C-alpha cells in the first residue's frame, strides 16, 4: 500500500544529464544569494541550488546574478553550484485545486494529497485586450444589502475592499462567498463562481480558523485557498497572487466564471518591499519601488469579463488593502485606488457606532455597472441612495442638535430606520428575493414610521410573514428578477399587510 | 569544526572573521572566541566569500585584537531543557543568571527551530477568565490564545502583565514560560523574589514556571536570540513534555528594536522608520513557532512598548497580523486615573461574540461601545458648549457613559500596593450580570464616584453607602 | 545504480513498516445504536380531552 | 401544500376579526402553523436514510 | 477513515526513517568505494555520448 506507493516513487527516479550552466554562490546571507556565472540564465527562470533550494532569478548582473531564495539560508553554502531548472516559474492550473488549500508553489498544504490540475501555466500571463472583453451583465450579490445596492458588483470587475485592519476584514469577503453559495448550489455553471481566496501574510492558525469556517459552511468544495502564510518567503508572497491569477485564468479561459479575493495585498507590498531592497533596488515611495504600480496593474488587469468568444468566462477580482489609519494617500493605497473599478471603504468608527458591517458608504463607489445587480433591486434601491444622500446632509444638521426643520427631521427619522436595516451579523447573508421586500418596505417609507428599536424586531418578523403568506411573491421575484407593476402592487399590499400589524 | 579564523574586522558587534582555512561554515552556525572574558559566542550570518564571514556577536565586545583565532562550534546554540530547567532564570547560553548553579537538564536543544506547519496546527480557543471585568467583557481570553498589549513605556505594561500572571498563571497548573526581553534588572529581581515567595518557583522545590530574562543593557544580538532560546524552552515543554503551556513575552518591541539596530550594520538597507526589511520574516517566524498545535496550544501574551505610542509604526502594525486578541492600552486613559487603563474601543478578541460569549454578552458589550463612541462624539459639543446645552436624551447617555467609565476603574491586585487600593477581581459570570443592569440604568442613579475605583455592581452599591457616609 | 542500491536494500529490508490494529479502536468508533422512536404519543387521546373541551367550549369569540 | 392549510388559516384570521375572543384557538392555529413548519423544516432538513455505501 | 489515513501516514513516516537507516547502511559499505567506479564509468558513458 504505502510500500506500493514508495515502490512507484523509487521507480520514479533514475538518470540525468550534463549541466551546461553553473555558477558558484558567493554572497549568501540576507536570504538572497548572488551567484557568479550563469549567462544561459533566461530572466525570471527557476534555478535549482545544489543545496536543494530553488530560487528564481529576478536580477541579472554581469557580475553576480541575484537569485532570490525560496529556501533556507543555512542550506545554501557559498561556492555551491546552481543548475538552471530552465523553466520560468509555472504552477499547475486546473480544476483539481477546487477544495484545496495550496501554498504559493501549489503544493497542497491541507495535505489532501496531489492536485488534479489540467495544466501548468506561467504566472506572467498578460491581461486580455479591449477586443477580448465583453459588456458586463453578470450580477454578483454578496448577501449584504448595502454592497449590492450601493456598490453593485459585476464580474470581471475589480472592487477594492479598503478600511482598517481585521475589522472583520476577512469576514466581509467571506459573506460574499456565502451568498454566492446560492448561485454555487444553483446548477448554472457560469453563475457558479469558483472562489479563490488568497491569503498573504497570515498565520497558519488564522488560516486554519478560516478553512474551518469555510468547511463548516461547506463552501470549501468550490473554494480554492491559495496561501502564502506568514512563515512563507517574501519572493513566494510576491509570486502568490500571480500564480493564484493563473489558476483563475484557467476558469476564465474555459468560459467559467470565478472570483478572486486578494487578501491582503498590503502584505504582498511589504514582501516586494523587502525583496527589492535585498535585491538592493533603490527604495520607492514608502520603500516600495516605483514599478510596484506596474506589478500590481498587470496582476489586477487579468480580472476581465471576456468576450462571448472566450466563453464569457469572467474572473472577478476583489482586491483587499487593509489601510492602516485609513491612510489612502500611502503610495500603494493611492496606486490601487486608481487601478480598481470600485472602492469599498469601511470605517472603524462606524464599527464602534455599532454599524456592523461598518461601511463608509460616502467613499464606497462602484464606478461600473448596474447589470452588476438585479433589475428589480435596481428599481427598489433607486431612492435608497437618494434617501441616504439626503440623510447625510440631514445628519450634519442633526449634529450640534440644533432644532431641525420638520422636513429635515422627517429625513432623519426615515434615514435612521434604513441604517438599522442595513446592519447584518457576520456569517449570515441574505437571499436577494428576500432583500427586495425589505428595501421595498423601507424605500416605500412604510418603515419610516416604525420605531428604530423595533426595526430589528420588525425585520425578522417581516421575513417570517413573507415566508408564510407572500412566499408566492418571493418566488416571483426569484423567477422574474425585475419588479413588474403587478409585483410592485402585490408587494405594496403585502408590505402594508405586515407594516400595519 | 576547527575552522580557524582571524577576526579581520570588529566593526561594532558585527565582527567579521576571516576563516583562514577554506573549510566552509554555514549560516546560523555558532562560533566561540575564547578570551579572558571566557567564551564569546558569535553566530555566522553572512558568508561574504573568500571564507570571510560576517557574524553577529551575542556576548559583549571590547578588547578584541584583529587576527584573533576563531573556532567554529557550529549550528545553533544549545540551550538546556528538561523539567530541571523549571525554576531557573536562563541567559541565552543556558547559564543560570539567577545563579542556581549549572542548569540540570535532560536534552540540550538548538536555539533555532522550524515553525510548525499548516498540517501540524490544531487551533482551539477556550474561554479564560482573568478576573478583570474590562478584559473579560471586551476581550474574553482563551486557551492557546494570542493576546497582545500595546501599552506605554512600561508605565504599567509590566503592572498589567504582573496582575495577569498573578491571576491566570497561578490559576494555571500547567507550564508557563516568562521570557522578558530587554527589560530592566529591578523588574527581574522583583519578579524572581515574588515568584520564589509565591511558590510558583519553589526554590528547593519544583516550579511550574520557568523564566528567561534578558536585560536591556545586554547587546542587541543577545536579545534577538533570547527570544529564540525561550521558544526552544517552550517547544520542549509543548512537544517533548507535552504539558499545557502558557508564555508571556515583554518587551517584544525590544525584539523588533534589536533587529533594526543590527540590520543596518549587517549591511541591509533599513526599511521605513529605520526598521529592518526583514522585520516581517522575523515577527512571522516567531509567531509561527509559537503556534497552536495538537502537541500543545500555546497561550501567548505579547507586550509592545509602542514607540512614542505610534501603532501605525510598522512594528506594531506587523504585530497585529499575528494576534487573535489585542488590548491596546492608552497612556492617556491611565492619566484619567482609570486602572485598568486599556483603551476600550481598541480592544478586540476573536472570542468576543454573540455565541462565543453569548448574545447577551455581545449585546451588553455592543451597547457599552456604542455609548462610549457617542460620548467620544459628543466630546466636541460638550467642550465647545456644555452638557446643559446637550439634549436630555444625550445627557442621560453621557451620564451613563461617565458611570460606565468609572465602573471600569477597578483596583489592581499585584499593584494593590502600587496603586495603594486593594485589588478588585470580578468573575466573568458576575461581569455579564453587572453590566446588563447598569445598561438598563438600574444602578444609574447612584454616585459616579461610587462606580469609580471599585469592582462589581455590589461593590459599587457598598461604596455608595460609604460615600453616603 | 544508487537507485537500484536503495531500491533493493530498502524494499527487501522493510517494504511496509509494522501496523497495530488495536490502536485504531481508540481513534475510531462503531455505529451508535438506534433510539427506537416507536409509535408516537396519541394526540387528544381519551374522552378526558373531549369532556374537557366540550365543557371548556362555551367561550364565544365576541 | 402547506400553503392550502395556511391560506385557509389566515382567511380564518380575518374572519376571526368578526368573532375575536377565542384566545387559545388562535394560539392553537399559530401552533398548527408552527408545528407544520417544524415538520416541514424536519422533512426539508432530512438527510439520506443511509451512508454512501457505494463510494464512501 | 480518519484513523485509516493516519495509519497510512504513520506507516509512511516509520518506513521513511527505515529508509534513512538503509541510506546510512549504503554509505558505510565499500559500495561507497565501488559506486565511485560506477559513477566514473557512467560519466565516461555519458560524456562520450556528449
Image (cartoon, coloured by chain):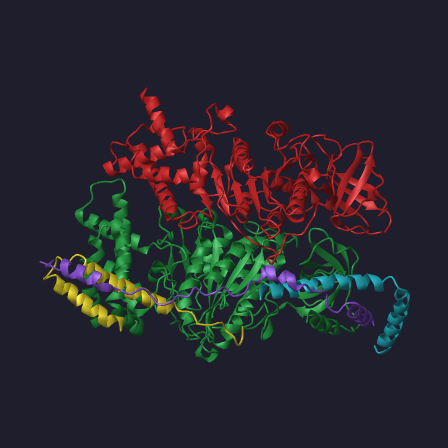
Query: Residue at position x 69%, y 68% from top?
Result: A42
Q: Position of residue A291 (x, y in %)?
A: 56, 58
Q: Chain C's shade in the image?
A: purple
In the rendered image, the residue lying farthest to the top is B469
Question: Is residue B252 among what the camera can see?
Answer: no
Query: Residue at position x 74%, y 44% from top?
Result: B108
Q: Chain A's shade in the image?
A: green
- Residue B222 higher or lower than A279, as above or below: above
Image-based side of A30 in relation to A129, left or right: right
Image-based side of B18 in relation to A136, left or right: right
Residue B335, by quadrant, is top left
Q: Position of residue C16 (x, y in %)?
A: 73, 68
Q: Nearer the viewer, residue B390 or A459?
A: A459
Q: Which chain is red?
A: B
- Residue B407 higher or lower than A158, as above or below: above
Query: Residue at position x 28%, y 45% from top?
Result: A396
Q: Chain E's shade in the image?
A: cyan
- Residue A176 higher or lower than D54, as above or below: above
Residue A18, by quadrant, is bottom right
In the rendered image, the residue lying farthest to the bottom is A309
Question: Is residue D37 among what the camera can see?
Answer: yes
Q: Quadrant of the C terminus of chain C?
A: bottom left
Q: Position of residue E48 (x, y in %)?
A: 87, 77
Q: Which chain is yellow?
A: D
Image-based side of B84 in relation to B257, left or right: right
Amino acid at each position: 500500500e504505502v510500500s506500493s506507493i514508495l515502490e512507484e516513487r523509487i521507480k520514479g527516479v533514475s538518470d540525468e544529464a550534463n549541466l551546461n550552466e553553473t555558477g558558484r554562490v558567493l554572497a549568501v546571507g540576507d536570504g538572497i544569494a548572488r551567484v557568479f556565472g550563469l549567462n544561459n540564465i533566461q530572466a525570471e527562470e527557476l534555478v535549482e541550488f545544489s543545496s536543494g533550494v530553488k530560487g528564481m532569478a529576478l536580477n541579472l548582473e554581469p557580475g553576480q546574478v541575484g537569485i532570490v531564495l525560496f529556501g533556507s539560508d543555512r542550506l545554501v553554502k557559498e561556492g555551491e553550484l546552481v543548475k538552471r531548472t530552465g523553466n520560468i516559474v509555472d504552477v499547475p492550473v486546473g480544476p483539481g485545486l477546487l477544495g484545496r488549500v495550496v501554498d504559493a508553489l501549489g503544493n497542497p498544504i491541507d495535505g489532501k494529497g496531489p492536485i488534479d490540475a489540467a495544466g501548468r501555466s506561467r504566472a506572467q500571463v498578460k491581461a486580455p485586450g479591449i477586443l477580448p472583453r465583453r459588456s458586463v451583465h453578470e450580477p454578483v450579490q454578496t448577501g449584504l444589502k448595502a454592497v449590492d445596492a450601493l456598490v453593485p458588483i459585476g464580474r470581471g470587475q475589480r472592487e477594492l475592499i479598503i478600511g482598517d485592519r481585521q475589522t472583520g476584514k476577512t469576514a466581509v469577503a467571506l459573506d460574499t462567498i456565502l451568498n454566492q453559495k446560492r448561485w454555487n448550489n444553483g446548477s448554472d455553471e457560469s453563475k457558479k463562481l469558483y472562489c479563490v481566496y488568497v491569503a498573504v501574510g497570515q498565520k497558519r492558525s488564522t488560516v486554519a480558523q478560516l478553512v474551518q469556517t469555510l468547511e463548516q459552511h461547506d463552501a470549501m468544495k468550490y473554494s480554492i485557498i491559495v496561501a502564502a502564510t506568514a512563515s512563507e518567503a517574501a519572493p513566494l508572497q510576491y509570486l502568490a497572487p500571480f500564480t493564484a491569477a493563473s489558476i483563475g485564468e484557467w476558469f476564465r479561459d474555459n468560459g467559467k466564471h470565478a472570483l478572486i479575493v486578494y487578501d491582503d495585498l498590503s502584505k504582498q507590498a511589504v514582501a516586494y518591499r523587502q525583496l527589492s531592497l535585498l535585491l538592493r533596488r533603490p527604495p520607492g515611495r514608502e520603500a516600495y519601488p516605483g514599478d510596484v504600480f506596474y506589478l500590481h496593474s498587470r496582476l489586477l488587469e487579468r480580472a476581465a469579463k471576456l468576450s462571448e468568444k472566450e466563453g464569457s468566462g469572467s474572473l472577478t477580482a476583489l482586491p483587499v488593502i487593509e489601510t492602516q489609519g485609513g491612510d489612502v494617500s500611502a503610495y500603494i493605497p493611492t496606486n490601487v485606488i486608481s487601478i480598481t473599478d470600485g472602492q469599498i471603504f469601511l470605517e472603524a468608527e462606524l464599527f464602534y457606532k455599532g454599524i456592523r458591517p461598518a461601511i463608509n458608504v460616502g467613499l464606497s463607489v462602484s464606478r461600473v455597472g448596474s447589470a452588476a445587480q438585479v433589475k428589480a433591486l435596481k428599481q427598489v434601491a433607486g431612492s435608497l441612495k437618494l434617501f441616504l444622500a439626503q440623510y447625510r446632509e440631514v445628519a450634519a444638521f442633526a449634529q450640534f442638535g440644533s432644532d431641525l426643520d420638520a422636513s429635515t427631521k422627517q429625513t432623519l427619522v426615515r434615514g435612521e430606520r434604513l441604517t438599522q436595516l442595513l446592519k447584518q451579523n457576520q456569517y449570515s447573508p441574505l437571499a436577494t428575493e428576500e432583500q427586495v421586500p425589505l428595501i421595498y418596505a423601507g424605500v416605500n417609507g412604510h418603515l419610516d414610521g416604525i420605531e428604530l428599536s423595533r426595526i430589528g424586531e420588525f425585520e425578522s418578523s417581516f421575513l417570517s410573514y413573507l415566508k408564510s403568506n407572500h412566499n408566492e411573491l418571493l418566488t416571483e421575484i426569484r423567477e422574474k428578477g425585475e419588479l413588474s407593476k403587478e409585483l410592485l402592487a402585490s408587494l405594496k399590499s403585502a408590505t402594508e399587510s405586515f407594516v400595519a400589524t | 569544526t576547527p575552522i580557524t579564523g582571524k577576526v579581520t574586522a570588529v566593526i561594532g558587534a558585527i565582527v567579521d572573521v576571516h576563516f583562514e582555512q577554506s573549510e566552509l561554515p554555514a549560516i546560523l552556525n555558532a562560533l566561540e572566541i575564547k578570551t579572558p572574558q571566557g567564551k564569546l559566542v558569535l553566530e555566522v550570518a553572512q558568508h561574504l566569500g573568500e571564507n570571510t564571514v560576517r557574524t553577529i556577536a551575542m556576548d559583549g565586545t571590547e578588547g578584541l585584537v584583529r587576527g584573533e583565532k576563531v573556532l567554529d562550534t557550529g549550528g545553533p546554540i544549545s540551550v538546556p531543557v528538561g523539567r530541571e530547567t523549571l525554576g531557573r532564570i536562563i541567559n541565552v547560553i543556558g547559564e543560570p543568571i539567577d545563579e542556581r548553579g549549572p542548569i540540570k537538564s535532560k536534552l540540550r536543544k538548538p536555539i533555532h527551530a522550524d515553525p510548525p506547519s499548516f498540517a501540524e496546527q490544531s487551533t482551539s480557543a477556550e474561554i479564560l477568565e482573568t478576573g478583570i471585568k474590562v478584559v473579560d467583557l471586551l476581550a474574553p481570553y482563551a486557551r492557546g490564545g494570542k493576546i497582545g498589549l500595546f501599552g506605554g513605556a512600561g508605565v504599567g505594561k509590566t503592572v498589567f502583565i504582573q496582575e495577569l500572571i498573578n491571576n491566570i498563571a497561578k490559576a494555571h497548573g500547567g507550564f508557563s514560560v516568562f521570557t522578558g526581553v530587554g527589560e530592566r534588572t529591578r523588574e527581574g529581581n522583583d519578579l524572581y523574589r515574588e515568584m520564589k515567595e509565591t511558590g510558583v518557583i519553589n526554590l528547593e522545590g519544583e516550579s511550574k514556571v520557568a523564566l528567561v530574562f534578558g536585560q536591556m543593557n545586554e547587546p542587541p544580538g543577545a536579545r534577538a536570540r533570547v527570544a529564540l532560546t525561550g521558544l526552544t524552552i517552550a517547544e520542549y515543554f509543548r512537544d517533548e513534555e507535552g504539558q499545557d503551556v502558557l508564555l508571556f513575552i515583554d518587551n517584544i518591541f525590544r525584539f523588533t528594536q534589536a533587529g533594526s539596530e543590527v540590520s543596518a550594520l549587517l549591511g541591509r538597507i533599513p526599511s521605513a522608520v529605520g526598521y529592518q526589511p526583514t522585520l516581517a520574516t522575523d515577527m512571522g517566524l516567531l509567531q509561527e513557532r509559537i503556534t497552536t498545535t495538537k502537541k500543545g496550544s500555546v497561550t501567548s501574551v505579547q507586550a509592545v512598548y509602542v514607540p512614542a505610542d505610534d501603532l501605525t509604526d510598522p512594528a506594531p502594525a506587523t504585530t497585529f497580523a499575528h494576534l487573535d486578541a489585542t488590548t491596546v492600552l492608552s497612556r492617556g486613559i491611565s492619566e484619567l486615573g482609570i486602572y485598568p487603563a486599556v483603551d476600550p474601543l481598541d480592544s478586540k478578541s476573536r472570542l468576543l461574540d454573540a455565541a462565543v460569549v453569548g448574545q447577551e454578552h455581545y449585546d451588553v458589550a455592543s451597547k457599552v461601545q456604542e455609548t462610549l463612541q457617542t460620548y467620544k462624539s459628543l466630546q466636541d459639543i460638550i467642550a465647545i458648549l456644555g452638557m446643559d446645552e446637550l439634549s436630555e436624551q444625550d445627557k442621560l447617555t453621557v451620564e451613563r457613559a461617565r458611570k460606565i467609565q468609572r465602573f471600569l476603574s477597578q483596583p489592581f491586585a499585584v499593584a494593590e500596593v502600587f496603586t495603594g487600593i486593594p485589588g478588585k477581581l470580578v468573575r466573568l459570570k458576575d461581569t455579564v450580570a453587572s453590566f446588563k443592569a447598569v445598561l438598563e440604568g438600574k444602578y444609574d442613579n447612584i454616585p459616579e464616584h461610587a462606580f469609580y475605583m471599585v469592582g462589581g455592581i455590589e461593590d459599587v452599591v457598598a461604596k455608595a453607602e460609604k460615600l453616603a457616609a | 545504480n544508487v537507485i537500484q542500491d536503495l531500491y533493493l536494500r530498502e524494499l527487501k529490508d522493510t517494504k511496509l513498516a509494522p501496523s497495530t490494529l488495536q490502536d485504531a479502536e481508540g481513534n475510531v468508533k462503531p455505529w451508535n445504536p438506534p433510539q427506537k422512536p416507536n409509535l408516537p404519543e396519541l394526540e387528544l387521546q381519551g374522552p378526558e380531552a373531549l369532556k374537557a373541551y366540550t365543557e371548556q367550549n362555551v367561550e364565544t369569540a365576541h | 401544500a402547506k400553503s392550502a392549510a395556511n391560506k385557509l388559516d389566515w382567511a380564518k384570521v380575518i374572519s376571526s376579526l368578526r368573532i375575536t375572543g377565542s384566545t387559545a384557538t388562535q394560539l392553537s392555529s399559530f401552533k398548527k402553523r408552527n408545528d407544520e413548519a417544524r415538520r416541514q423544516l424536519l422533512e426539508l432538513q432530512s438527510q439520506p436514510t443511509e451512508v454512501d455505501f457505494s463510494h464512501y | 477513515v480518519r484513523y485509516e489515513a493516519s495509519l497510512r501516514q504513520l506507516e509512511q513516516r516509520q518506513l521513511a526513517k527505515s529508509v534513512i537507516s538503509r541510506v546510512q547502511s549504503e554509505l558505510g559499505n565499500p559500495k561507497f568505494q565501488e559506486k565511485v567506479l560506477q559513477q566514473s564509468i557512467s560519466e565516461i558513458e555519458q560524456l562520450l555520448s556528449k
